[PDB]
Amino acid sequence: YEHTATIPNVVGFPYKAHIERNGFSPMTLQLEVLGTSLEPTLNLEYITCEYKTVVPSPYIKCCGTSECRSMERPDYQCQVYTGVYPFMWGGAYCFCDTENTQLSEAYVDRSDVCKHDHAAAYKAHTAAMKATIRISYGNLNQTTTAFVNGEHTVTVGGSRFTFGPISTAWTPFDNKIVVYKNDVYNLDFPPYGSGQPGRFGDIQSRTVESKDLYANTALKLSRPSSGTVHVPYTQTPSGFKYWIKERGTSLNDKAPFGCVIKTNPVRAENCAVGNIPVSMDIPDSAFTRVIDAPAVTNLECQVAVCTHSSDFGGIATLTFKTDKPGKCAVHSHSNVATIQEAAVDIKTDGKITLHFSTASASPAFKVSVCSAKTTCMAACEPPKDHIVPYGASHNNQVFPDMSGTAMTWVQRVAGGFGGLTLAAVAVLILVTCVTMR
Amino acid sequence: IPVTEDGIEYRWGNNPPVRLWAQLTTEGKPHGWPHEIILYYYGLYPAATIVAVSAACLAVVLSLLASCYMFATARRKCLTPYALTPGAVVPVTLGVLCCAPRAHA
Ligand SMILES: *[C@@H]1O[C@H](CO)[C@@H](O)[C@H](O)[C@H]1NC(C)=O
Image (tube, rainbow over all chains, first blue to last red; front, side):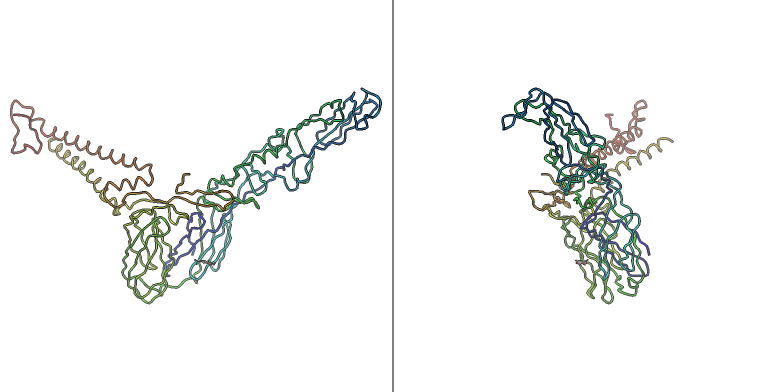
């Protein structure tokens, strides 16, 4: 017997689902959402890290003949200098002055901690969300794990569950992201084509296989002075260090729904948005027939206190005649107010207590006992006046009952002010009909 | 710091995060005399409630003006002709204040 329902995607929020197939005693289902998560698809464009400026020992050759060459390793700067007269602790070496060759070369490479201190870039895509759900009913209580995608099953027993597609996808991730040591950012990086010398990804090398280490760090050599041996060059500092120093305000403190983010499968956990549908099939052997626990008779309700909106303040009393004791499911039909307790036993006295909660001031819920149902309204005045350190346990819909007991006189005075106009219209019609003749 | 019915987080140093959100609170009796119902309904949801009060006042004044104008038009169509005719008076016994056409004699 398939049945459908919708549950708000709020962690730590009990949900009631009552099944009312005829010919059997109606029962209830407790739904709990325990740490839903979301995971996107990754692409791993390229990797960033520091650069090492590999500069070999300078070449002094005392003949004056030039020697120029250029290999294929990245960003050689083929510079040769003539007329240099180097010095050394032994005073000087060689004899000829103004005829010497200085060959100084340098390039860049990755660092030794590139395996560890590197940062990664990724692209966003369609994202699939984990959902860990706890299901319970009469003498059954079990957890599971699903996909809440278009199709999936649970099979907690003889019953099966399917969690339909998500209502919407307000993913905190978007377009392209950067991942670095247990943290992500929504920073637009330059593409693989090129990058500015120092902003970010000055090295835009690909995966750790270390092939085609592109670099645009803008080397520039200079002529050494006549004092001693020199290898002068100009080199802007690494942009990776500047980006690390600035960092700040990680995406963990920027989720638009307070959605704590982890990093192992780059996942985001424990955030509420939209609602999830559900369709469940329950076997006929999971419940008793109508021949058990008939407790209809007559029924009336009373409310003691309704200190509302905090955890549970709606203390209600139910009185009724009944047959032999047994179990009895209870719920609320309307969603104005919601109760906490699931199916509750009945004693021969016929008096039971319920704890409901609401957000309005004149609730008009219809509490239904496992076979009957009656109207039940309360004078729910007292507004709790503090600030709560825990979660909510009711729907946010607040509106006084149309009939109610609070705004009745406002409605009747408005009706009277309308009635004066109606009587004026009627007397005008009478007068004009009389004078038309 | 502000706080609403949604939630506020904490990160003060290295302590575990703390989650708080505001209550429904407000003041005034919610099931008493007329001049606290508005205060209760206004303290909660400060916006769109004075709009409701203004709309109700506009409806009331429109109803009053419509009733007054209809009464005036009915009175005119009732006994304007007796203001006509050479001389003549109001029947009085047939009507003197039911339609109230009193203007000297
Ligand atoms: C289901 O079992 C767990 C076991 O730890 C328990 O904590 C939980 O309260 C049970 N559910 C209900 C509704 O009692």
